[PDB]
Length: 174
Image 1 (cartoon, rainbow, N blue to C red):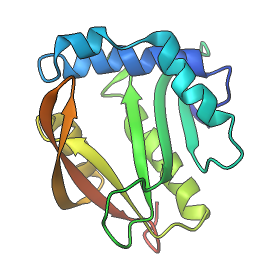
Image 2: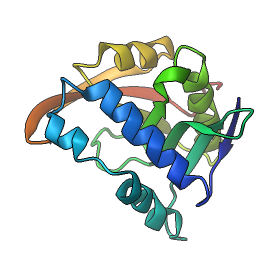
Image 3: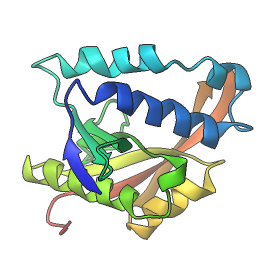
Image 4: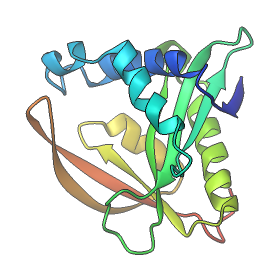
């Protein structure tokens, strides 16, 4: 496929990948009410307003099938509030459609977004992952992202623990 940045016309598609991949991944880990509480439209909105904001450093990428379907998705940007000095930007989200997993699209999406952040000259990057997600965690280790620490969060009222993986975005060659 082709990994590319995305505009507003991509959002709807990005939305389906988010919700569909969320539901198919966190079910049994995140309360069903939450997942069933996810929305295609509202989600599109979420990424909608943010795209339309000159002051927003966010960078969105999108995997595109030969058909032209948005199947992959990743968003990068300035570390929100991680709290790990040296780590300037973080990978906010990244999801590949279940039927498109184990195809490379995840590292594809990953590199593109890192290089961009690398080019824009960012120090280091970090991604917050869930622990009851040995799959995801496995991924970022295939990439080298070393462990920083954990964190208690809350989804659908559930208390989940996240874990961060740091990536030298500087001199490192991506």
